[PDB]
Length: 288
Length: 288
Image (cartoon, rainbow over all chains, first blue to last red; front, side, top):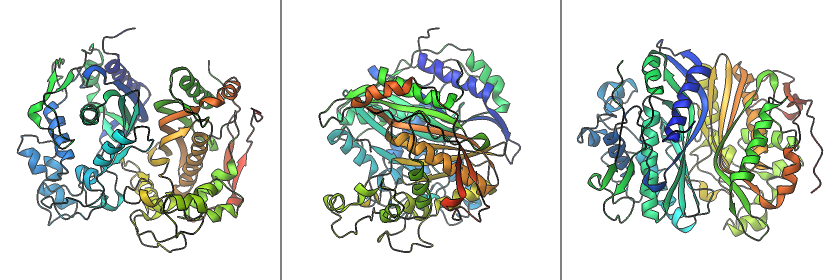
């Protein structure tokens, strides 16, 4: 019946649903997945709560460093590698780039992905060492202005889905857009994730938009509300079902709370040292 | 427990949930709303079924003609008016245009809306009488190629959300994006609608993407699967509650079926005379 962390329990029920009601496919590699097309869940962000899953740990440094890098507008994966965050290494390496025909592209130059679109949508991409200041639509700045000045708006949207630029990206954005919404002094967010693995990328992006919503709420002087996570192809790998069945039997801990330890001048004024995560309790590792 | 048309019944339950749980934005242009942020529903498209609501009739001619007009890349509202379809008339009229600063635009020139983005994303908009061939990304052609050639793809997306062009549109698009998905020889679709009235725009867009999915399935030699309708701000007007309550007590009829009465060369080869709608039975208009 009742769980201390009902929001994570509902996530586990989604995973169970995929295993029971999804469809098995094998892609061109012989790689097996079980999928449901179309899912949606909600997470309370009140009182500092951030939905960092507890039944299978999430790579917090990766979430946090990637998000600051997105916000900065960077498209240079080497900047993450300098921080020992390797999540974009394979997608920016020589071999991956050359397979896409990007044979003159510097290693780690991801093309006009995520943060370039968020801060410079429509600008002419050159490389990941170019100053784009003042170029393109600063969607993130706009969202913040709308939230502060026009909180009733039904139009508060940010998207990295830029058809004109997809061909130069190492891959299309996975979290393709988000919409913000304000009511009774609280900031809510809905993201759309076109693809993801319930064992890895879904929890990772859940956490990243939880963090982003708390950051924007601080910038805008609002309280956090609800995070809505919408999925396209929600899937698990068929070879992981044993590991998943382990996860499913675990009782979630309460989510941790986020704390920002100094004032910020703007969304561009966060640094890793001042983002604190309190009381993250997590279950042990899950074998193969 | 189950109903003849369970899919429509689940829509009714969404409306009931907004009435019971939603939050109010009161005003007094008599336009207050009751809202939930983040909803999702699904509709089976098997065997020709198209989800045109039965408990409150949907304007099918409008749905049909608007979608053929979108597909054509048109942005000239006068083409709809010539078919006796008036849904875009107020947003293209002289006063509406002038109030946006579009003082030199021809009446009915909606700007770079929907169909222009679908067929020419990134092209340089001029007017609603300009040829844009070869200009911008033909997203609709790309989604059809992917369905046919890469049915496994998790990247099959079309969007009118173009930050660079929003300021020249009469309205930003309401259905902001959709994703397609292929399994077991069947085509599914998920749309994202950032805002809508459960009583009007939501059912209209439900029907439009149902039709689109049937059309694309025919082009691609597939069977129709499921339509997923995801909402941002899902709302009803507080002054329609009495009507809604009558409506919510009605037992839905089976949905009608679509029938295409000739072969098509491509997605551009449909005409209204070959799209038949069979057995669209509705409950009566609620007078109030």
